[PDB]
Image (cartoon, coloured by chain):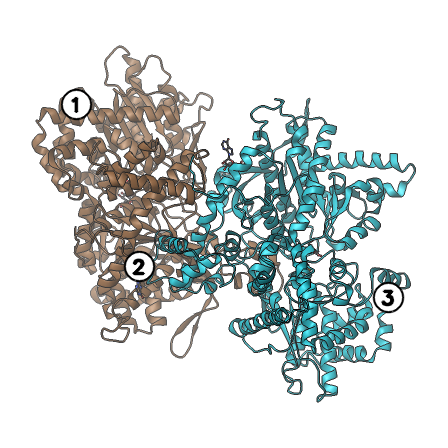
Chain colours: A brown, B cyan
Amino acid sequence: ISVRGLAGVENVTELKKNFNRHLHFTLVKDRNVATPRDYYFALAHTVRDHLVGRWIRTQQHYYEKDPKRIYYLSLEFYMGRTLQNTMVNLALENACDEATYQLGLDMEELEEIEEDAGLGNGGLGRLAACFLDSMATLGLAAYGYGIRYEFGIFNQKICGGWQMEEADDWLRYGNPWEKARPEFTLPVHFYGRVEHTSQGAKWVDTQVVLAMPYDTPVPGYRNNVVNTMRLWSAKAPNDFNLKDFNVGGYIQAVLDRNLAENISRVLYPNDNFFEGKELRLKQEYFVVAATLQDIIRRFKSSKFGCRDPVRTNFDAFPDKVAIQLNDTHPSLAIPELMRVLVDLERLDWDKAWEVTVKTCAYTNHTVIPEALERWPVHLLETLLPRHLQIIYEINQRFLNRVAAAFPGDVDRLRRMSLVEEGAVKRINMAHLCIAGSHAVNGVARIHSEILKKTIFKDFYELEPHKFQNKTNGITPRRWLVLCNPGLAEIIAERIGEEYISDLDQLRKLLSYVDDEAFIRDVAKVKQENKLKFAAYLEREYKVHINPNSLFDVQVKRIHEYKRQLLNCLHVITLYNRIKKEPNKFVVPRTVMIGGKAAPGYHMAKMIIKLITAIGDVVNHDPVVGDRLRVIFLENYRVSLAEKVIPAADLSEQISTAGTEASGTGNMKFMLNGALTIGTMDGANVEMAEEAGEENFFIFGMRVEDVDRLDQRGYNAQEYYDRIPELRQIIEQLSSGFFSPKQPDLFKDIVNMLMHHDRFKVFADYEEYVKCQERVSALYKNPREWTRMVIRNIATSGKFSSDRTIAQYAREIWGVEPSRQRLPAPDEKIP
Amino acid sequence: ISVRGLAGVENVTELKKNFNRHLHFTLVKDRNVATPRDYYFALAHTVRDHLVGRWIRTQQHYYEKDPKRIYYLSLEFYMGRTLQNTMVNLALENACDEATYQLGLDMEELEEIEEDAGLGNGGLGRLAACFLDSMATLGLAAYGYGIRYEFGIFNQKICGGWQMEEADDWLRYGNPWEKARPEFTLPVHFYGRVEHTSQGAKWVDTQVVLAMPYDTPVPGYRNNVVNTMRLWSAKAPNDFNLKDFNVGGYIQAVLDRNLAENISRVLYPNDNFFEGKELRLKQEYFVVAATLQDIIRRFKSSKFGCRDPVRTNFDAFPDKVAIQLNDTHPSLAIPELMRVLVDLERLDWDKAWEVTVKTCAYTNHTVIPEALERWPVHLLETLLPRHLQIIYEINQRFLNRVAAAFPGDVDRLRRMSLVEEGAVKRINMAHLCIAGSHAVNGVARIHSEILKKTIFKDFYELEPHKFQNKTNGITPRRWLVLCNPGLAEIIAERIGEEYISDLDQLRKLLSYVDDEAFIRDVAKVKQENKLKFAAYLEREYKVHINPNSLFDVQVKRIHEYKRQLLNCLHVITLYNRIKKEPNKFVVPRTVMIGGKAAPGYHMAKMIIKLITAIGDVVNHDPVVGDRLRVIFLENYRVSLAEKVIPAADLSEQISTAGTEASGTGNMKFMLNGALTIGTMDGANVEMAEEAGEENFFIFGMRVEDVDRLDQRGYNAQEYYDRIPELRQIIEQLSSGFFSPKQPDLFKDIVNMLMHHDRFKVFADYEEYVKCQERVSALYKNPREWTRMVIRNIATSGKFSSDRTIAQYAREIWGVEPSRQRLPAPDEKIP
Ligand SMILES: O=c1[nH]cnc2c1ncn2[C@@H]1O[C@H](COP(=O)(O)O)[C@@H](O)[C@H]1O
Ligand SMILES: O=c1[nH]cnc2c1ncn2[C@@H]1O[C@H](COP(=O)(O)O)[C@@H](O)[C@H]1O
Ligand SMILES: OC[C@H]1O[C@H](O)[C@H](O)[C@@H](O)[C@@H]1O
Ligand SMILES: OC[C@H]1O[C@H](O)[C@H](O)[C@@H](O)[C@@H]1O
Ligand SMILES: O=[P-]([O-])[O-]
Ligand SMILES: O=[P-]([O-])[O-]
């Protein structure tokens, strides 16, 4: 059937009876009233059963051996569905497929019932998920720590072409994967005040909110390692949230508990944008405070909680603990770690600081100013009074280090300050993370250089040893074996299966680049994938597309820097050229654009309306026929990504050079047989460098060209004046050609494009359409297109998150990866 | 070990492996980190497994045979713990005891870990629970319908002698018994307006809240019948509660969902008191609306949803459906049933009314005015506009019936109106229930007569056939076999086990009233029970009591009509007599008073403080020694009741004649070996009548004496003037003898007692202490006391809820009870 594992005789029979056990005892249903949802749950519980045994020994193991622990703190974990992925990592896919078949059910139909775990916005959240999978696969004693939002990223609905947001009630039917652990509930404090008494400061009169943990298993690829993802939930104490007496109402007091519990209610839907709301800061301290207590408790047991030097010596803390900060969201971990060590454990400042710097590491994800976290001091002052004091003290001693290094450089002092003066005083969380971490990394080579050359230049001059790079990656399990079994099978037919955990081996595929059978096969799976997607489209969304056309897809969050608008300009150009010479041949294309816009991002929402507006005109023009369709992919999310990427021919990674930190969608497309048209931005540079620029469609300004243009001054009128095709398009938008009933509907877009384009869309227009003509030319030559595809696939090995994690481990965490199978799952009950 | 069933070889081995399965696969723990709480859950899941098989066939059975369905609507279901009770009804107690023992665990220690299901206030809620158990045991196709409050009756804490309320987070650790059924979620409407168009009225522009059901199994006693208790939970729709667009905030919209969900958040802690709050009315319509849709859906399938006359003829609705209204809380079921039939199904008013009257029956629980539900019309007008219209129309046609029956009687017309004029117009929910039900019953013979003679006199004259009586009862399973196995065993040693489901057989115990061995045994279990309670006291609450003394206990909600104050007066009298003649012998007594006060009931909270105040003085008087202790039983609830009742010698049922509808605690004491000192109130009359007044300690005014006194006019000064002992006590309270630091602390109690005692405490004082002297005299004669006890126990059979349910069934519901074992639980998978 494929190498989805063995469909053993004993195991298929075992699966079936367990499926029935659960349907009866766990779901309390009888075959006669069972719906597909019940069947999905019976299977999920059956599958979950296979990894609890491994989960328990894995954790018991780490307790016995006591290795260095890796704690990955992130406010986002974009997980997606977990049934198939669990089957894949346990080599259960074929057995379950067989078993459910014999039970008279379609496994694929049941998989579609599982709700996505959308506790993420985009790139950053998905990175955390891929990292978790790789850390388990590389056998590291790692823990994912975050917030269990009861409402994830909103579900996007398109009404009259506009995006409508609706609550993502993903827990509505239950989550069979998590395990509530109410017995490890921890208290978290807010507000209060600071008392300075005799031997130390005291955080007093605080409001207590409880953090209840939920553990979800994270299985490594076929190695019997099951790590843990602990997600905290907010709970109100039953005392003060009722006991602070003297009138108000007993009923109201109980109803008011949903005020402390709102902390974990919903995920903020902002991607690369900072919103200084109090609820957000509360979520940030909430995940940090609870997680650190858990980390320290585990450390206090280790082997020190037995003997060792005997004396809770935190000198070995850094040798047993490593906490990675996914962006500055968990930045409070730095002053909080200081607070505990100093205020509670009573260590001296300098010893505490040495420990904190040695255990914390920070990862930066963007260079745009509006994405930077700068928290108003008055907020920190009211909510976390002692942390503000600690931050001021950290700033004081840091700046003294600067003044000592650069005597007299008074401007450098203010530039580097963690405290920003002005309208309102703010705290620069990034400056905080650089100062309190022993490593700061970028997510792609060029982004990492930009950090040293620009944004964190002063910091780099002060401590060059801190700055590193760790190019992002994706997990080949979910992003290849899971979403594209057809491609994984033919690759395996030639080079084996070892590449699933050693992607570098894909290079061996280079020797089949002239193999007639392989070229036929690679091309066949892509055709099969496109047919399946074209079908899903009519099934669930309804209104036909042509599977013979080129599948041009751009899927990612809607942003001005991602330039979906530049894509739009090209689509309209193709339309206008067809209307000019109708009977002239052009390569057919289905251009699919999908992504979510933050609810408050007006421009982004205006762009989604433009996309749909173009499709209204283009898709109903009889002269155009089937040569060009514009489709907007609704509710783009992880599970939808697993469907479109394997069916894409052209991947669009066209952000303005210097704005996209790295990107990971680009890597997903490269590994699944799509050719890339993009700018020399983020990881695009490394991809092109790996596959060879000849097998890549690069266009537009390089970072240097952008800077030259800024020195000069960007004037969009110039481009409007010298390019008639561009001019024609702008006058089409301005006159209501795409919005008949509301002729001035797109005035904000035109106005912006001409007068405030921060991302110079026009400057790359000519080179973009010129470059698009070249891919059309190559698509007309099936054999050469496919041969270039093989060149990309065969060279994508470097972009596996296993390579990324192995580097973090060695160069930052100080631990050695291991592909050693844990001693089976075998029963055992001590 | 006892007749807690057989500890079979095969079944004890089976239990143990299943215990381990769950501990591993379900709780995901390993023996090395398992705590008693985990062990309790492993057992609970194991026990729950044994009744799912039965649960599924029971429901499948009712679907096949299609009998008349009994729907018990109540806003309260005072369930308590369910582990032991499930073991008892499945004959699993000894097997589980053995199994856990072999596993090295104490079952009793694990049972104490289960949290109580306190979805009730007192008498009314507990009645519903006992009824459920009996309906299952009598094999009726009955369904309990209510609200799944996430916070039940508050946990009571005593601080400095005052009651402190604290949220009852009973779901904190999970509920292994319930089964969420998100697939049967139903919509409920609120607000909106009424449109009158061409062919009918339309309830329009409403706010939708979703009702999600949760099913808990209700097992009959050893008959393999497992009925269902469906509890609704409020959920916000993900559309409008987000989709009603045009600014406000995306985050706020999601956070605001906890406004529709507040409907099922907490139970109102009022016992026999009406609070006209909007949240309450919303809970009331919420349980009613969701339940009726469920009832009709089930009816639409039956055998009509196949053929029959063919034409949804609701003429047979009353022949297949019976809905019992537990008080007027679910009274909206009447106008709601009308709304559906008329507005949706389009039946004519008169046919709809005939159907509604024929399927609804109402049970009244009290005669005090402040406990009556009179909802302000402006509330109904805004929240349920169409129901108000229906109610007005019901009133119109009802009153026309009255005028036709009593021509010219204009005052009778206003007295009987469902609409009350005055300050604000209100709707009398009780008048509504009488008019729309074919049966109205009281809960005790005297209470039922009082309803006909007083409160509902006019209604009785109009339709005498509607008024019935159904004396309350308690379930002998939880209230005998579960809480007092020692007593159940010795009874069984003599007359067998058949009495557990046929309490009448306890009469055979009369022939052992002179049996020397039995008297020794009855007395022995009571001594064993008192010793165990005296121990629990020091274990969990700490500060000694004497097990040789008389256990004088009064446990029930704190009320002015229950007269805990009269008890207090007696306690202080005993104290003063001892201080007068210290070296004189008196029978030692431990008087225990327990119960909860509604948070807003100031007087009730003042009484709890008085009780504790008396204990502060009495319990520390060296001259008193061990002859008198005053203890306040903290957090009285179901599980605590199972502990005190079996250990009580004297039961206090001293409410003012005519105020206690029935009472059930009195029956629990009688069946467990306690003698009763009380007034001729509620069921006390029937109990005394059954055991013989010679074996009962009756005192005080009878209903007639109370009325005579009211004609005359109650003047407490008179009693204060002629009784020196009483006078001494009042001057003790007035001068701060019981409150040194705050001498005027109890001024409200004294003031009330002397000037506004609605329950004439003083009028019964003399006869109460006189009567108390008589029980002390009899307690001095162990053999005669025990012989009287045997006379009570042997005569308590009539107070089983099995007798009560059999009468409801035959005389109201029109169904025949059956003690037929359902065809085993045996596997099966169709
Ligand atoms: O005190 C202990 N004794 C024995 N095993 C322990 C102890 N603490 C942790 N463990 C084991 O380590 C796993 C890790 O627990 P955690 O990391 O503290 O959540 C547990 O599930 C146990 O198998
Ligand atoms: O349409 C039906 N076909 C077969 N069995 C049914 C059907 N509806 C109800 N049942 C059975 O009756 C039980 C009662 O369902 P309910 O009373 O509607 O909640 C179900 O769990 C099934 O065993
Ligand atoms: O680092 C993970 C991702 O974080 C953010 O979403 C960046 O915009 C993206 O470029 C990067 O790939
Ligand atoms: O009917 C059940 C119970 O309802 C109420 O709690 C009444 O006060 C009580 O007398 C009665 O026994
Ligand atoms: O993270 P990028 O692929 O939008
Ligand atoms: O219901 P009663 O025993 O307080």
The residue that disc 3 covers is B714
Q: Chain of mark 3?
A: B
**Mark pair 2, 3: CA separation:** 78 Å
Residue A431 seen by the camera: yes
Residue topped by disc 2:
A432
- The residue shown at (27%, 12%) is A581
Question: On residue B691, which mark appears?
Answer: none
Question: Residue A431 sits in which quadrant?
Answer: bottom left
Residue A778 — which label?
A: 1
> Along the horizontal axis of the image, is A107 left or right of B591?
left
Eyeballing the image, is A302 above or below B589? above
**Chain letter for the residue marked with disc 1 in the picture:** A
Of circles 3 and 1, the one toward us is: 3
Please tell me in which quadrant of the rendered image residue A609 appears. top left
Q: In x, y percent, where is residue B137?
A: 58, 48
Give the secondary structure at mark 3.
loop
Provide the chain ID for the residue under circle 2.
A
